[PDB]
Length: 66
Length: 66
Image (cartoon, rainbow over all chains, first blue to last red):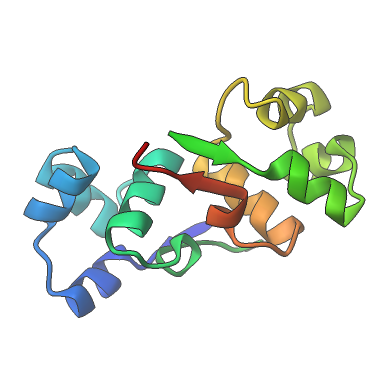
């Protein structure tokens, strides 16, 4: 449903999940799970990622009718 | 935290909460709760709205540092 480009984007950012998770105010492991597509982040977390990376949320987490 | 423009945006679309709720696959009451900002919709729900309303998710649900 939702495709997570956070890791792909994060690599562009060259930001560690360590700091990004901090922006989110979640554990680094939380990002890794998100990167490793274990689960998709909540809207608040997604938005925080979008806001903190000032990147479009959809670009990071796109919902596809797939 | 997150400001919901769904009601503001949806009405621009001319889409009923009911159809959108259907688009989301949730009840109208749920959307009305979302629209009346009782609670913020999940990431999947928000993204579906973004797709359905052909509008950016953040634009509908903006996460503010407030």
